[PDB]
Image (cartoon, rainbow, N blue to C red; front, side, top):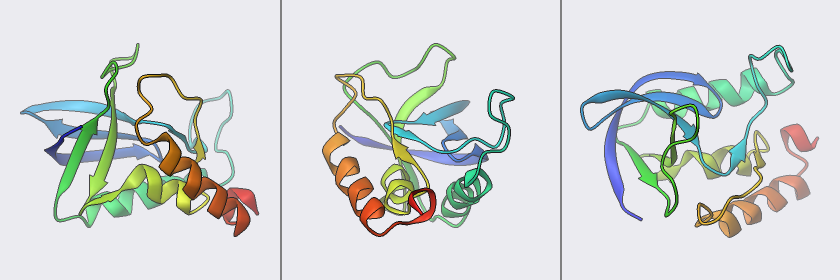
Length: 135
């Protein structure tokens, strides 16, 4: 997998962000993680959703460099969102959310599962520390 640069346009909630990627606006869904939702009536504002949302937002808005990394599988979902690991100054936001107890590892779809193990490790640690959704 290689990293490519991108530029922030707007964070939408914890696991969806709009970025400028190779000249175009594009909506990206973070791979392998589910954060609580700030929207969707099927839900509403779930607990830790505003928190997950502000955490993704802040990491992205205070970054020097943002990079997107596609996995080995399909690169967009049925809604036209890019499916990617997103990095702020070299730190993967998908892992940072999970390590903080602000996201669960999602149901995994091969072959888009390259960082699955790593994420699962961080989720078990957050669970052990009883952080945020695990509290």
